[PDB]
Every structure is written in C-alpha cells, then in structure tokens.
Image (cartoon, rainbow over all chains, first blue to last red; front, side, top):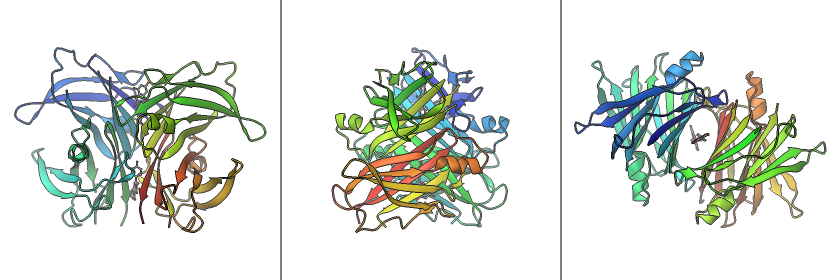
Length: 109
Length: 116
Length: 109
Length: 116
Ligand SMILES: O=c1c(O)c(-c2ccc(O)cc2)oc2cc(O)cc(O)c12
Ligand SMILES: O=c1c(O)c(-c2ccc(O)cc2)oc2cc(O)cc(O)c12
C-alpha cells in the first residue's frame, strides 16, 4: 500500500497493539477532512489505509491515539495524541511511544 | 516561566536557532484559539511565552515550524511541523518544558514537567 | 531467528543499507568475544545472526558501525558507533540514526 | 566545563536523578582507561567531570548506568547501560553536552557540541 503506520511501545518493548489511528487530508478550506482510519494489529502495524489512486499529492495528517493506549495500561501520559503532518509528494510512518515522550519517523522508499 | 520550548538539531549537534513556535489553546467551542508565539534563541530556547496567571488549565497545542528551519538550511524535510498537544495544569499549576529533537525525516518530543 | 537488527536513516528517511554490525558475547573474563556479524540489507535489516541453540542466556553487545555509514554519505558524525548492551534472558534491536544522535529500541516478542 | 552529561526519564517526564556515569578514554595500547565519574543531580545534570586542561584529544566513552536507575524504580529494563563513544577535540577544544533520554526498552543519546 501507499501508506503504512507502525507503532512501538518503549515501556514494554513491544508492538503497540490496538492503537487508534486517524488519517486526515487537508481540504481547500484549510480544514482536515477524515480520510481513513484503523487500529494497529498484534504486530503493531496498520495496513490498507488507502490506495495509490486515492492517495494523491496533498498535505496529510495522521493522528495516533496515544493517550487511550496509555490509559488502557494504567500509565498516565502527557500527550493527547501523536500527530504527524506531511506533504505527500511508499510511506511508512513509524512511531515510538513513551508516556512523556514520542518520536515519529518516516521511511519513504 | 510556566512553559518553555527547547529545540535541538540532530544533524549538526546544535540548538535549533530561530525556529518559529506557535501556541494554541482549545476553546469552549472546541476551536484552537491563538495563545502565544515566538522564535527560539541562540541557545535554541524560547522563554517568556506566557505567565502563571494566563496559563490556566486547558488543552494546549505547541506547533514548531520545523519545515521552515530545514528549508533555510537547504533541506526538504518530511514533516510540515512538529506539534505537541497536551492537557496542562489539571492537577494544579506546573512548569512545562517541551523539548524537540529534529532530523530531516524524524523528530522526537519530550516533556519535562515540574512543580514550582 | 532469535536475534534481528534493523537500522534506519533519519536524514534520508530510509533504511540504512550496508551498515556493519558486530555482535559480541561477554566472556567469563569480562571481555567481549566476537559472536556473529553482518551488514544490513537493502531493507536495512540484518537477519540470520545466530540460532536458538547458540543464543544462550548471557550479556550480549551489538555494535553498529554508524561512523562508516555517515562517512560514505559525506556527513560528519559524532559517534564512533552505536552500542547496544543487554542481558539475553525473539529480539529485534532497532536503531534510528542521525549524525549527532541515535536511538535504539528493543522489541522483544 | 568541557563535558556535561544530562539525563531524562521519558516515563515520568522528569530529570533522571542519581544516575551513575562513568567516563573512559582510549589509551595508547587501545585499552579503556578510567577517566572520570559521577552521579546526576536533582536536575539530572552532571557537571564538573573534567577540565579544559585534562580533557585532551581522544576517543572517549561515557557509560550511563541506566539499569540501576530503572531497577531502583522497580523496572527490569532491556539495556545494561547507555554508552556513548566519540572522538573529542580533534578540531580543537569544544564543549560537549551528552544528553540521554531513557525508556525501559529504549534510549536515545544526543550530542550538543559548541565552541567556547
Ligand atoms: O520504521 C521502523 C522503525 O522506525 C522502528 C523504529 C526504530 C526506531 C524508532 O525510534 C522508531 C521506530 O522499528 C521498526 C521496526 C520494523 O520492523 C519496521 C520498521 O519500519 C520500523
Ligand atoms: O539540553 C537538553 C537536551 O539536549 C534535551 C534533550 C532533548 C531531546 C532529547 O531527545 C534528549 C535530550 O533535553 C533537554 C531538556 C531540558 O529540560 C534541558 C536541556 O538542556 C535539554
């Protein structure tokens, strides 16, 4: 697929499983229009978000619902979510998660 | 001050100087209202954004203009910006340091939260 | 395999390809004995380092030759290498690379 | 001072206090010779490790005892330690800040290098 999301748990040394992910595309309004969503799998991956035809050049945002994930683990987190915003010009967006920290990386091949 | 932003360049091993930072607070109607803004200094720090009085409980967004920083250095980076969104002061007033470490295709953000 | 190494390039948004990796096992001497090595593939992965039988409990070190990688790219780096040292009690050791920074993460499933 | 170490806890969003740090320098015979040591403070900083005179050109190793820090907090972490290995001062004297951000199954290290 044109776009993949991968999430990791730095506390537990594991894939971050069942994490909600929402993808938005910026409308001509300058508002975000919902585009695709899903939850990460047991391998911490989310696949099948979009297709090559659909995934045109644009400014896209991916919101990962980190706070819900931490809440289910009974660990109190800092962020509301982790947002990745990029201009789409294969994208793997990877996120590594900690309660008071996250990093996000793009692997574009 | 209650909120501080610090930015680092992971490519040069330096502070990230002259980076724009825009801060927003979630309104009653769920909109993001402009709250404060500034540029990082020679040390890559931004101080004086707000005050103990002004910085009330709320959901806040700190948006760091990473793209402009990379572009001025000749790089076309992946991200539009780095944005940090968090609930502040709901246990009482705290001091927040929002740190960001920048790479062209990656960034990390960390919060150091302390009690006056 | 029991042990996998994965390397990413934060400057280029890509797998870190052809990066030298050496694995050591701590001897009763308190010295490191060479154990396995390889170079990362076009996908930035290094597989087939060891086998379950061979990979007994121990304290292991994985040295990733980051400086050579940066040198080939004509970007001057800070570290001599990135070293990961752990007690082995499936391990994926992932490294994300920048010239003056790296992070390493373990995913243990 | 020429070399400073700073450590942060990515789980609690605080400085990592009372963390042991051991510094080594590569000898002529290729062995690692003990060079300096200390513990991080309340701010998670370690200052005063060395001096402009002492801190000559060389390959240096900074080993941060992450395992003991996690264990005292009840966590069994992945890493034995975080170790940073670098060539120092070969362009002339510099000031080095070695920063580490800690998680139980992950860590990152960054260097901020500046010119007196
Ligand atoms: O892309 C990936 C990635 O980034 C990480 C990772 C490494 C360091 C980080 O800081 C964050 C994530 O693990 C991965 C593991 C995979 O099997 C595949 C990947 O593509 C990634
Ligand atoms: O100098 C600092 C620094 O380099 C970092 C840092 C940022 C991102 C990381 O991933 C790791 C460390 O945090 C800091 C946090 C502070 O409150 C004060 C600092 O001076 C630093």
